[PDB]
Amino acid sequence: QKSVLEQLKQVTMVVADTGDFELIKKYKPVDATTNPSLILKAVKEQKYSNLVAETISKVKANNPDLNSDDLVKEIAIEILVSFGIKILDVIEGKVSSEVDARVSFNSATTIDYAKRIIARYESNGIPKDRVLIKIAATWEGIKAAKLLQKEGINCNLTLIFDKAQAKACAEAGVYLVSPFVGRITDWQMQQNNLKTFPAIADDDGVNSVKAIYKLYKSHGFKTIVMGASFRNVEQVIALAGCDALTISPVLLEELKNRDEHLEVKLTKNDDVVTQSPQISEADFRWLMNENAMATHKLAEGIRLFTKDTIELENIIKQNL
Amino acid sequence: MQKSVLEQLKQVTMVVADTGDFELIKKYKPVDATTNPSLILKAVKEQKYSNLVAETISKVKANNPDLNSDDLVKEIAIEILVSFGIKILDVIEGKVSSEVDARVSFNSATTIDYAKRIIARYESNGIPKDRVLIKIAATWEGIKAAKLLQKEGINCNLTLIFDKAQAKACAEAGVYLVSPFVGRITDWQMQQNNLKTFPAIADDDGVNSVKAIYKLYKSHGFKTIVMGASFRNVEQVIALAGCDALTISPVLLEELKNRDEHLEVKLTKNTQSPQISEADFRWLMNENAMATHKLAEGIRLFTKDTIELENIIKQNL
Ligand SMILES: *[C@@H](CO)[C@@H](O)[C@H](O)[C@H](O)[C@H](O)COP(=O)(O)O
Ligand SMILES: *[C@H](CO)[C@@H](O)[C@H](O)[C@H](O)[C@H](O)COP(=O)(O)O
Ligand SMILES: [Cl-]
């Protein structure tokens, strides 16, 4: 008689995927995740209009010497952080905040942006252990995360569409990876103009996370596997037992209202640990190129997040 | 004397034949010729070259008795590539382009190794490096490899060029020649807009890519040769009359040979910025959805054809 959501929480760390903090409390997730598209969506909700306006005025008044370009950048990071803090107010776990997608191919500036995010959280009275820095899993992002982790800054490597990509992240000692499910299912359906979701056993997105989970547990990697991007509740249910799953409020609502028994599908084991050679940059780039879907979706994800980041900047400029 | 469009084109652009079939080249009298893994595969499968392929298989196997099936197959493949190149050099005054194994496209060190191996095979057959261009996919790693190869006196043909950023980086690396694709860019344009007919020449993304690269190069004083490649029809070739060079399929060369109207020259001659960084190159390439897709798929396609050649070799060993 227990909801599927409540049962899921006992075998998987449930995470809410949204910037709309007022919707989080009723699902009581452990952690929460944001991204540039979710922040933009929240910024355009009338209920957060004053939060945005206040942030713009505060940063503007506190930084009278910054040139207009730098001012807009500061406001954008403060908005990202402001939503993150409102989220932390209603959860006991961590919040993921993503670096500017425009630095995705530059490890040095990714590190800079990551530290700036942490600095803003700290200036606002939040300890860094409550925050995960979200970084696109390009070779450069992974390289950046490797350095950040060495300095005690936990990262969430996102836009993961390939197993070799996930392996490189684990080898860099990243705290958590977000292999995508839904966007892979999108590719699969679009390839043949499919009108209905594939059967779970045939869902490329679900199988991607299953393969990454199996890889991690067989290699003793401690990086947390967090499935992200979902199109339907069956995809979430098929991954019950995964370390974590970040889920939209719409799907959390469906899970909360279903009371069927939930069977765990992903489980850890005590098998002999496999030790393997490290993935070099050249091998990573080759393997990614061989995966047509992965190369396309990683590139597209960066382009789309960039578009939403630029839209936010334009909103800031139009209200400065 | 009235001259065909092909003959008129030769006076304002270096005409290059895009084929592995040397028997078709002499007829059109191009200056240079270009091959690629797909063209070599098609040539290897022809019956007229079945005798040529067979001899190479036996020749290599006799001189390499202890090499495993893996190394033997790869050695036969490189000698086959060079054999077709040498037969092409017999019927032209200029250079031939031979492409490195597409599988090393993201490894500068092994790209350099393969390039040097090709040059060494030509030299052992009495062909000096001046007659050869090494084709390399224009990934960041390929460009870095070409930069070093050029310093060693090995001329490179940077291929699978779909964006101005690649072209800029190639020119900055001192590469001998770049091959911007025209046809594949237009393919993208037509799929994206669900076009039924080809776009007007003025709006043809492929043609405009070469025009832009040509303009960039001449305005900045880059000496890298601009060679348009991959064409869907003769109108696209004609639209680039005046370009440094154009590499054209035998089918389109035949069409040009039979066209008799006046040819209007479209490209003519008439600034220096800091060199593009790896990070800026990667960003610009990512912003160009078409370029990222076509470069990636181009490498995948050439790889498939390289693997097929190995399969033909293994079952005929
Ligand atoms: C961060 C991953 O931990 C998370 O916000 C992701 O960015 C989202 O889960 C995906 O972007 C969702 O994508 P979709 O295509 O909307 O399903
Ligand atoms: C080398 C470029 O100098 C040349 O052989 C190229 O590989 C070909 O021109 C293109 O690959 C042909 O592409 P298409 O899509 O067949 O037109
Ligand atoms: Cl792509």
Image (cartoon, coloured by chain):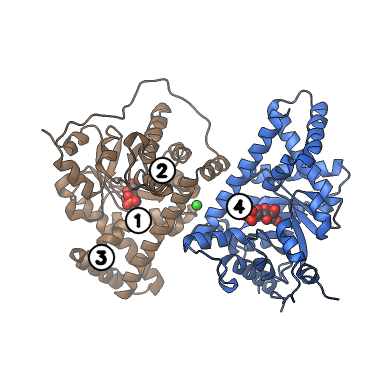
Chain colours: A brown, B blue
| Mark 1: amino acid | Ile
Q: Is residue B66 above or below residue B301?
A: above
- Which residue corresponds to the image point at 15% horizontal and 39% vertical from the top-left? A258
Q: Is residue B280 left or right of residue B44?
A: left
Q: CA distance from mark 2 to mark 4?
A: 30 Å
Q: A2 or B264, which lies in front?
A: B264
Q: Is residue A19 above or below residue A176?
A: below
- The structure residue drawn at horizontal position 20% and vertical position 64%, both measured from the top left corner, is A48
Residue for point 32% across, 37% down: A199
Residue contact between numbered discs 3 and 4, judged by CB atoms under 8 Å = no
Q: Are the residues under marks 3 and 2 on the same chain?
A: yes
Chain on which label 4 sits: B
Q: Is residue B257 visible to us here?
A: yes
Q: Are marks 3 and 1 on the same chain?
A: yes
Q: Quadrant of the N terminus of chain B?
A: bottom right
Dot 4 and dot 1 within a common chain: no
Q: Amino acid at mark 2?
A: Gln
Callout 3 crowding tier (Cα within 10 Å): few <14, some 14–19, many ≥20: few
Could you say whether the residue bearing mark 2 is in a helix, strand or loop? helix
Q: Which mark is residue A117?
A: 1
Q: Earlier in the sequence, mark 3 or mark 2?
A: 3
Displayed quadrant of residue A20? bottom left
Q: Is mark 3 within 8 Å of ligand 1?
A: no
Mark 3–mark 1 Cα distance, whole angstroms, equals: 22 Å
Residue wearing tag 4: B139
